[PDB]
View (tube, rainbow, N blue to C red):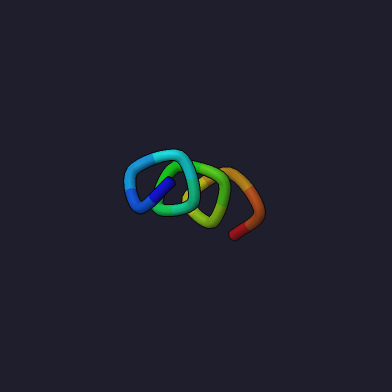
Length: 13
């Protein structure tokens, strides 16, 4: 989950 969310955030920003 940690990495999944890191990447999600990267995209969102």
